[PDB]
Length: 133
Image (tube, rainbow, N blue to C red; front, side, top):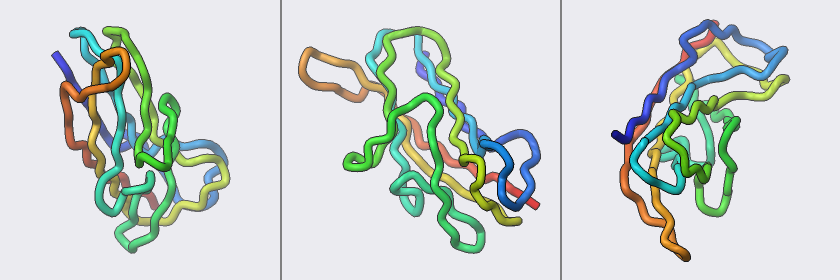
């Protein structure tokens, strides 16, 4: 019922100063069963909303669909609906990328609301690696 697909850009990205926004990873989340929302928690070396290169450089990522809350270490979206949500984790135009492989690790959490509080009903560890030349 609950499902999470997470994946590197299936395309090819090349290094240098990116002339447009570019998606590093796609993030798709959905459940028909009832629910209030979704959050992505960047774990490990990714804490803070980063991907990390094979060389050790940390590059910030943005979410198309979700709001970023620094003090909690998560992105979140409130959404009552049965449709897969498709989000892109991307870098902004102007971001300098290197010829290397970038890694992101996180945890997606599905929750439900109860008038005052939210409560986690499913959870999945996501992980991926995207290469550039």
